[PDB]
Image (tube, rainbow, N blue to C red; front, side, top):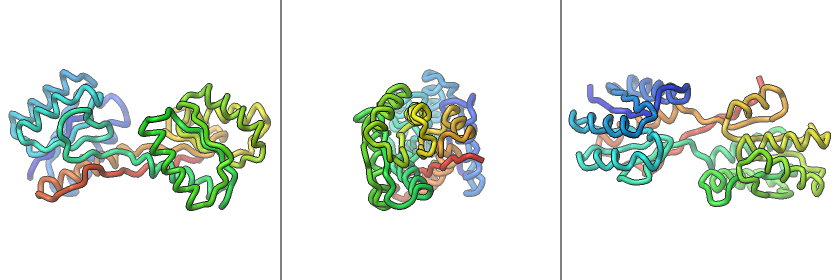
Length: 271
């Protein structure tokens, strides 16, 4: 069997273990042998991992960077050895990458909007709490949410940035509540902003307003479990790993692949 190499940022966290497990599972399915090197969250260890792989003549490199800005030299070493690079979750600031695989933020915003339409119905009155202006997260999530607005003809009462921060989310929500008391649902572009908004609604005595967050952070999860937050959107690490291998399979075969492959996210509701 041919070998696919995965350099993972770390293995000290469940998210990264799942990524490795999904890669492994897809490797087994497609008949490949998977080499896994743990960078231990250290950029020096990451560089040495790639170097180690280049001396052995690995055919493809799947790399989940420790930090986007730290990985460039490791990527260029792979480029110099003619070893195709595929990045997972975080991009490489520098270096040539054949394909990048990550959670689709546009799809995520759309999912959040589809869920608002599911529970609050077509044409609902909504408020969007946006993230830091200029970030890819705020832009993509807002883009996905706009698709939902167009698909479900939502009445967007307001859309204001709260810069991915809890306190600003609360203040902005409190402000917009005085202006639009008939708001039916809120799409907050991160869990922190969703939690701030929930506090504002709680203080105002409005528990009927359906709030959807994004990230699936422990606190966002907690808000869902406690029955306060309607939903949050979580990344699927196993599938990033899987899509990575699937794309590596195509690259190894000589197929011309896309620069980016979107990975689904899942809705997280109370159980």
